[PDB]
Image (cartoon, rainbow, N blue to C red; front, side, top):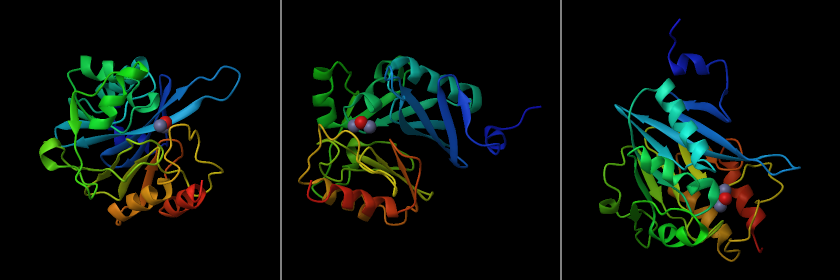
Length: 239
Ligand SMILES: [O-]
Ligand SMILES: [Zn+2]
Ligand SMILES: [Zn+2]
């Protein structure tokens, strides 16, 4: 009995080691990893895995190198294709905590130049390559070589100064990372590094950048429809 990962994922989300994987589209999966907070519920973070022909692309590490190695184990087991590159979406632990595991696997890594400046300071590792964004927010194509369907956009400061977002061309998906929370959220999570002045405008800019994305994927909520964007901006208004 040898079903494909897609065939297997019709049963629903799959637990794998300490992670959870969910198929969002035929070649797109959400990875979820958890930060144990002793005496409290574990903090979930989501990223993406994209199968782009004969290669795999990753958006965001897990919280730790070990959890990120578990992501790579899942990819080997279920997809059985090489991972070419990863894009990581700001210098917080949930997004860049596992860079060493990616680097050791021979994966080329990319982040906002600003993320690369902020990370070492915080005990993390910079990505190997720096993305530069035009004033309009779109990544300068020369700094994002061979990204396949990934379309990278800097929406402005919000959840952090360096937060970036990623659309997946040929799908209904755009990844807001930690900038966006779902349409029922009671808070924006930890705002300790947030730009409270600009957050709402940056959430709006993300929505305007990916107007055809009907599935919004987020770090700290399950996927939602576009109402998540204005809900997030409403929650962020006049912080
Ligand atoms: O975060
Ligand atoms: Zn963050
Ligand atoms: Zn986060």
